[PDB]
Image (tube, helix red, strand yellow):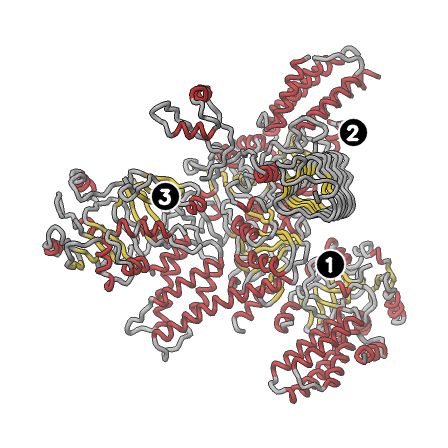
Amino acid sequence: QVPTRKDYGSKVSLFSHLPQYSRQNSLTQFMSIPSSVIHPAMVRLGLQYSQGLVSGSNARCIALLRALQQVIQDYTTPPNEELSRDLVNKLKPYMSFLTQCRPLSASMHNAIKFLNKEITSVGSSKREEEAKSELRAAIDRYVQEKIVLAAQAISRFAYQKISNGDVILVYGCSSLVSRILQEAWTEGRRFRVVVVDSRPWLEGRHTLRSLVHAGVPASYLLIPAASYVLPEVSKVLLGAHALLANGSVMSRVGTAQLALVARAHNVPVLVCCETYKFCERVQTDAFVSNELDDPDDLQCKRGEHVALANWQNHASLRLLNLVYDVTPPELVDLVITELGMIPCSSVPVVLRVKSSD
Amino acid sequence: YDLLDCHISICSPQVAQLFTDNFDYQTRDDFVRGLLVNEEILGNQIHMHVTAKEYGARVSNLHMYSAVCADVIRRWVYPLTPEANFTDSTTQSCTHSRHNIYRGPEVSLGHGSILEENVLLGSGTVIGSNCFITNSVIGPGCHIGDNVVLDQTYLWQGVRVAAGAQIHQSLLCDNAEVKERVTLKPRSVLTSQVVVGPNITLPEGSVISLHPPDAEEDEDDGEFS
Amino acid sequence: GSELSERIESFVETLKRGGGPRSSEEMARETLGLLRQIITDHRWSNAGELMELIRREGRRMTAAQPSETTVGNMVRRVLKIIREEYGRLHGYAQLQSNIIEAINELLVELEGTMENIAAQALEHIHSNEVIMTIGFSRTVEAFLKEAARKRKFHVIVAECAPFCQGHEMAVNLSKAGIETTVMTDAAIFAVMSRVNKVIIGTKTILANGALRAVTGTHTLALAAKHHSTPLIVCAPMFKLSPQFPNEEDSFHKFVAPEEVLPFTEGDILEKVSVHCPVFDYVPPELITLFISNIGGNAPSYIYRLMSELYHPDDHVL
Amino acid sequence: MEFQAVVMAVGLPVGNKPLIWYPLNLLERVGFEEVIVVTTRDVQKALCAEFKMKMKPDIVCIPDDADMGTADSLRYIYPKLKTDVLVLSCDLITDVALHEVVDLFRAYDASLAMLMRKRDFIGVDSTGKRLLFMANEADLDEELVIKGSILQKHPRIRFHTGLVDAHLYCLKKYIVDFLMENGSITSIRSELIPYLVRKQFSLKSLDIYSFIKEANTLNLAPYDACWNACRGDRWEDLSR
Amino acid sequence: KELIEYFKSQMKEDPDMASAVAAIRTLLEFLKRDKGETIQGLRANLTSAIETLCGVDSSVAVSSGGELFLRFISLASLEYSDYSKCKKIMIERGELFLRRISLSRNKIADLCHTFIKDGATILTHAYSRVVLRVLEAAVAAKKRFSVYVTESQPDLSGKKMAKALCHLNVPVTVVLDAAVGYIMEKADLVIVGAEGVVENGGIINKIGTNQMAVCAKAQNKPFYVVAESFKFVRLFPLNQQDVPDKFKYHPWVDYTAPSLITLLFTDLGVLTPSAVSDELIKLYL
């Protein structure tokens, strides 16, 4: 049915268990053009995930829920079966194909868990299209509140903290931090934002655009210049991708390093994360569970001295591009959630609130 | 369409040959527009080089002047930077502070004067109290008053700015002067010791010089005629 | 004569325009040859007149490029050599040949620096070790490429964001077979949990044990201090400078911001402030050990090498 | 089902094998369990009985009119299509792996995705996949004109001269809806290409994509490319 | 203004009485004297009452106790639909809550003095009744220890603490307030009384506390903080200016990082500093 993608390049000895694919090849070379095993919306989601077009975690979860809406809308019921078991038996190859396209983010895992909890809690007294419209209404109501209302609450809690004349440091590309800065600039705060970026995504330029289309004075620099700009920086605002059970912040790879330099410069860090990006899964390093992007992404254009062009001919050469890392809970001060300003030590306890217990 | 012209066209001496032959070719784009439309006569295929890691431009407007000056102050034409002093002159050497603030010798800043971004101060330019200077180049030997703002402005040598003056996106040439209670608008040009009297705000389109018909007007101790 | 000022001005605008030559040991040899050409093409009666002369041209050569300290400390070392010879001859005419043979001794000292560090390099590397370096330096890559002759270990060469010069170090160490791992600059604390020790180079050692180096290494020193891993600064003794850190704010060398944000970014380049410092400051408390050609020294010992190689009356130059 | 393949026949099996067999075999290799085939009626309205003599799993052969075009062929099968349209032709033998154009149709969610293989001057963006312009001097009074908005949004456009259309398209539902709502189009190769290329030069818009292959080439209706068809089928049909 | 007069009459009649419990008694008396059948009309009156109590008294515990009392009023208004029974419900529940609060200090003493070793050294800050209650329960539990109290310069109350401990006949010494790092190596435990606990686990106290906390951090000493449950504040001060400036007025309040605090000793028990955020998120302001 669905084969597995071949591992590209020479893997790191410390990252031998984690998969490392390539973007130049995809899994649909040995698949049907009218997609029979996987849904067409699911293969469209996998193609727009594997090529790097949708890389933000909120955008990934939103496109995943839209593809799930297209799956449920194009779903029929077979004889001698129930929806609550056939749907969970059919969605698991879809999620496994999505995992084989790209390692899933934590928001996608919690969306899968919430969808499983929702589609197993439907009654057999309901009809087919009645339950389908109920599940579609539950999906877009859920994404509506726990994206837009959570982002508005986090921005309102961040407006009463950002002062006038402040210097804010951001890193990476995210919807929530850029929305916070846009609403703070339009609501009355006068500040300037320092953008920190890292190779090879160069995605912070995106939110740099999101700082100049709103009229905020911005400053663009990279992670070696963070040590130079952090004496000037008063506050650091970060976009968390996943929060773990011990209070750790699983995020983009230049965050724990950036938080350590910010603590060394006595600048408090402020991560922004919602409850649906939490995890009961816990890790303490960036080695047991991490995403490995392409080894061919690290080469550069400095004249015509591309040294990492024929890197595979060297047998004793290893190439590694980490995506996510883990911050220790000793470094991060604030977690600004829609329930308020909590520390990292309150990350699983809110989960006890978010498990209806 | 992604090619900014730097006008650093390196040539063979056949360019001078074709300019000796064709008397109608007045400038460079005339030469290339006459060379490209006539190919089987005077063949001479022009080639091209594209630079992506180095800077190159020229100036022909106030817009090109302002953009190239803002790129020079923001060090886009490194190694050619004002604090490096590539022209060995003691009246032009500067020190590079944070946020691209270039400070010359004997400036004598006052209390409350804040320099935030892209400010260059020449030799002997005195600055008063409670000033606000940003994105601007100040010449040597100037005199600045009190409670002033100066954004995207180009003050040359010998100028004298009084107190309360608000200057946006303008250009002041040599030995200029401006009194109090003046506020300047974007794209204003002041040229070679034009004095602007009090309670006289200039519009957006404003070029005032000593020559009447070339500029918009000619000023005096009073700005009204 | 005139050819002396020809060569001096060529050296001055060579330092003003770009990096000529590329590495620093050739530049130190050029500086010592230029200084012996200055002392062999002039006339003086007292040593103090040549001292004032050398102070003036040292002021000129460091006013050409204030960020590069090798010419300035070489001028200061020649000044202390002249001061020592005048002190040992004062307690007259044979001074010039004494400074000539002292400069020849300094040249033999300076040509055999990297191979002396390589000879003492085996005292810091054990089998199956995880090494992380930053930037590109021929001393550290020569260190590792000859230390891999009898030991087998791992080197993680992290690139620096302004100019990814660690790719050259990676392809130079991978030819020797040291199992080189290539990473970015943002994953250092992501990989500091497994790196056993940090072996880096530098650009300039300061007087208090602090050092300027390729940018992003203060972050590496902070992460290695957080994980308590020792830092090995494989640095020669012509990168030793008496210039204190807080001195007229002339620390960092800023370059063009094209390598950070390209010119094809759009109209958003007007309302943005992009800085690119290629050097960074590391305090001595984040450094464990320096490795010079005379051996290993503490950061609590840089003042003794300072007083042994430089004079406090020549700090202003 | 994601696609419904439509094979056009407008002036046919003159060669070493049947000309209808290669597109259908290509379709039936990778999926395409049901194929809608349009029969020819301009030259002779009797090839459909020659079309139902193959050994495929399932074919849909319909009768057609003599004076008809490709746009009229898509407007004729409008109440029997419910998904995206993947257009083919008879004289098109291609060794190109089909999944590139479908990957470009799915990955960017394009409105039309087409395949070419090395008259008609085309301009495609520097990425090499998204086209921006295409024109010929059959309908051009002036030499060549380029819109200003596509130069402001895309500063470098690579032009190609020797590219020929292999007639392998990927239409969406609203494209065929606008084609049925606008009956002035007769040849879809000159209608759906140029009007959508003009409408893409508008933010929220449509995407047109193209794949320039370098493995094989298609054929022509005349006898200009009829000599290389046997040489292609003698060395390319052994693997298929 | 009868509210400030009743607050000063409740606070000045007993020197063993805190400001926060007097503010809660004043708020309960104002709610009993309001008799306004309105939810928002009572909420605005309570907010003006806490505005007067914060304009008069600049203590953090007064505004903290008023916010807890306002959250209790909001919970009792959201529970009962009709207001007529809800007024008596608020009155009885507030009287029972004040009865539970008035016995809190003894509970702290018997549940806190167990930690102090015999023959040890105590380091303590300025005057509060809670550390006196803990220490008198410790000497009632037959324990001997040497006490070093900070002189606490802005109001010389640590000398009053030392006088109250010499009347208790225990070895106490007024140590110089610039010498809390001098006697840190001999102080095996540092127990301190706080006047306000912020959400993450840090505390709001008198100005000489936080530096002592970092003296407890570099010298590895367990920095114990003792405070009740009505001092829980729904704030997050990041730096030292990020506390509200109305509680400062020479600063009067220092924010102490939660990493420098070993334990808390509240009415819920001996807690990690992460427990305050748990109580503040199930309390919901």
Q: CA distance from mark 2 to mark 3?
A: 67 Å
Asked if residue E216 is positioned above or below residue C194 in the image, the reply reads: below
Residue at the spot 66% in from the left edge and 84% down from the top edge: E38
Residue type at numbered disc 2: Pro
The residue mark sitting in front, 2 or 3, is: 3
Q: CA distance from mark 1 to mark 3?
A: 58 Å
Name the residue that disc number 3 marks: D124
Q: Quadrant of residue C294?
A: top right
Residue D1 visible to the viewer: no
In the image, residue B74 lies at what x, y percent? Answer: 61, 39
Q: Nearer the viewer, residue D144 or A227?
A: D144
Label number found at residue B154? none
Q: Chain of mark 1?
A: E
The residue mark sitting in front, 1 or 2, is: 1
Residue A63 visible to the viewer: yes
Callout 1: few (<14), some (14-19), or many (20+) C-alpha neighbours within 10 Å?
A: few
Q: Quadrant of residue B84?
A: top right
In the image, residue C39 lies at what x, y percent? Answer: 71, 15
Secondary structure of residue under mark 2:
helix
Residue at the spot 80% in from the left edge and 62% down from the top edge: E252
Q: CA distance from mark 1 to mark 2?
A: 43 Å
Name the residue that disc number 1 marks: E241
Name the residue that disc number 2 marks: C312
From the image, which quarter does the C terminus of chain E lie in?
Answer: bottom right
Residue type at numbered disc 1: Gln
Residue type at numbered disc 3: Val
